[PDB]
Amino acid sequence: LDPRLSVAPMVDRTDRHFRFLVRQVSLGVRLYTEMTVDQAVLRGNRERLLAFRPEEHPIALQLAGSDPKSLAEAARIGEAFGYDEINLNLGCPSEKAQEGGYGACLLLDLARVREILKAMGEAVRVPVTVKMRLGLEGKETYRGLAQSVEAMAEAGVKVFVVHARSALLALSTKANREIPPLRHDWVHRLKGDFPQLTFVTNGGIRSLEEALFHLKRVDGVMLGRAVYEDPFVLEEADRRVFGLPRRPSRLEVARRMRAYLEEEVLKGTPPWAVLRHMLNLFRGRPKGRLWRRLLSEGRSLQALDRALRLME
RNA sequence: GGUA
Ligand SMILES: Cc1cc2nc3c(=O)[nH]c(=O)nc-3n(C[C@H](O)[C@H](O)[C@H](O)COP(=O)(O)O)c2cc1C
């Protein structure tokens, strides 16, 4: 498991279509699914929810839930689908998370978190990891954070992805990634205190240069919004992070997405399910706005063909 | 089944 660089799990963003796009930009970057509730995996259509392309490796499935047995079985199923890692969501502050007692509100019950992780760890052979916040209600302490890390490590967890801020359950989800202050220094300190463990820091990191800064202090960096707002924020990732002699081209990626789009349309996928994630491919580039316009207006393969000729 |  290479922890150096990852794209954050993002509901309504990091579905298989956007993940495929990102993979065209960076071969090395680690991909995460949208948060997927365990009940959905158990009772829903597992193909629709879990199926992914082999090119997406390395890829982790993120699960949400509160019941050890349900999550363990969901992890087992996730493993069967070929995911390289089962990630436990411990950071979602949504109203639905609060009603279902999952996500960030699990940090109130370390005993429960430990039995969840133990059950998950015994159900699969792939790494079981966590994505967490610094605490709840802005009442977090460094000792409290370290204690939670210890509890989870006792349960077998080695990889800790930390959104380096508290969660304020009274605020909206959007506000919960803007208002609570970031404390990346705490994640830096965790690595200093738990050298044997793997720490990936997350929150407000806008560029590869900024990621490189943190990579001097922690094992990895996870980027969310910056990547969706402009996938080519990862343009130099393969070369500067992963030491690969590879540099993507926006036009090459766009051409690959066209062939991808044709395959998907073939099997019933709505064109917009793919195109809606391609709007920022030319962010801040010449004709980038017309590109967005053409795709958003046409929402079809024919529209993509017009945009491609525009950018050729 | 699901964090503007
Ligand atoms: C639209 C959106 C959806 C998100 N969905 C998830 C999710 O499903 N699971 C999760 O652990 N975090 C989710 N998050 C939080 C991100 O993973 C990440 O921790 C947060 O955006 C801060 O990182 P960033 O500043 O690089 O974007 C989501 C964030 C956004 C903006």
Image: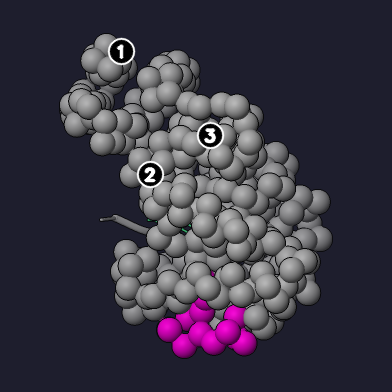
Label pair 3/1, CB-CB below 8 angstroms = no
Going from N to C along the chain, the mark reached first, 3 or 1, is: 3
Q: Name the residue under label 2.
A: A228
Q: Is residue A134 magenta?
A: yes
Residue A128 seen: yes
In the rendered image, residue A218, in percent from the top left (x then y), is placed at 62, 62
Please rate how many residues cluster around mark 2, counting C-alpha atoms within 10 Å: few if below 14, some from 14 to 19, many from 20: many
In the image, A308 versus A271, the foreground residue is: A308
Chain letter of the residue carrying label 3: A
Q: Mark 3 points at which residue?
A: A26
Chain letter of the residue carrying label 2: A
The residues colored magenta run: A133-145
Amino acid identity at mark 3: Ser
Find numbered disc 2 in the image and state the secondary structure of the residue it sits on.
helix
Chain letter of the residue carrying label 1: A
Q: Is mark 2 within 8 Å of ligand 1?
A: yes
Residue A99 seen: no
Q: Quadrant of residue A131?
A: bottom right
